Image (cartoon, rainbow over all chains, first blue to last red; front, top):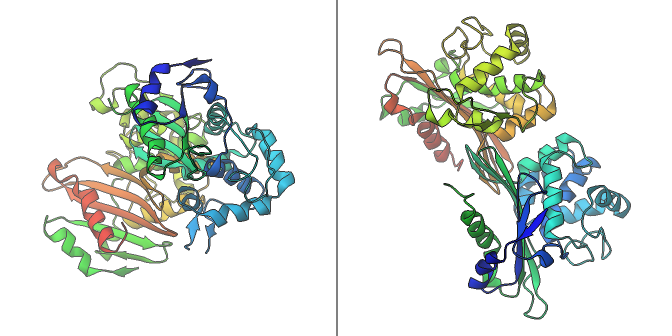
Length: 236
Length: 243
């Protein structure tokens, strides 16, 4: 069940932006958001698509194993290619997977509008593919639980590649995305999605915002952090 | 495996008797400050949580990656262990009573089998099923730790690849887009001035597309010197440009 917390709008206003945050404790049955309408609106996933693309890459055999090196401006591991800008790597993966297989996996994953038109190597960046913050949480929860239609091994491999913060009792798996800086009337979209394991609890999250100014990009992390901090998740 | 006498500099200041073993790419290319001590076997103390976790998973004693080890509200030796812990948490805070109970459930026969498969030190689990790695006769060298960890990195242990991956994520301690560290500390206790305890730091570092396996141990008779198990090897690694 998802509920609306309009008091969270203060954190978007303060900084002057239009966006949404979805935060779920334990499971996607217990979620809250600043804006119910926008929580279900679908946007270009941009680099958040590397999550399903890597899983599909591994399942189809296009990516050999966790230790494959993607050789070149620099050579990258799977983790490095996900965490850094590595355009050509994932373009090459998508072309190798192919449209029929890509379409079949997005069906199995219930990934957004499942519309991959616009070119096999750019549909998630300039094409027709769209996904909501709610659908991102649902997808990430399935991954967490090894419930996607993929081997547990491959789900595990991608999950370690997504670790971004680590402490003994606090672990964060996450991924950013950004379609580009658009204009005030035709803004781009920026994302931060993932999950936080704090002690024995887990929190799934998905954030997106409209971006029409290059200087606003860091808000994709700061706004969610501030909201999570207010919920008591960050530290004590 | 060559010996690097220049690395002794890092141990000289603190009068530390210890050894560091560092291997670039594979265990076929290693360096150490003390060739003799590199193969000398010591109590693994909490570094044993690595094989123990894998064995707990393989035998079904540990259900999966999301198992919660519930605290019963009864006193534990460390306040940091007095709470519900995940598998990763229990490893990271080195929650001894959690792993003692795992060991009991695994049992002597299964434990012996897996230590043989894993080529784990002297494979001597005498001393009581819940204390052999802490005060018993089990002994492993720094070189053996590097061999074992490399197997784990490569998914080559005789355990499911899923289970090896689960334990690998539980060992992550430092994360960045192109830098990742998997590691585990150990500390047997302070022994005596005459028969000192041992402290350990073991693990591996992924930097860009390279991997480095490492194991450190030292004699310890004063708990105040404990951070040197991380600081000495960190200084050696940073001086080699592993940062």
